[PDB]
Image (cartoon, rainbow, N blue to C red; front, side, top):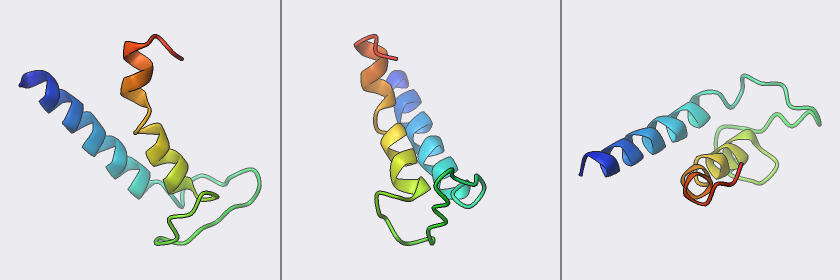
Length: 63
């Protein structure tokens, strides 16, 4: 129950950092989405895809 707490804490902190740092990085195509677009071009959807795909890469030894 400590391990899931570590999983949910890292997932909460990852989704919180992708919410915070969406306007920080200038993307290479010049994306600049808004705070509530939730579309596939934006930083937040790709970054929450990164915080969705970290645990499955760790068990199955994917980079």
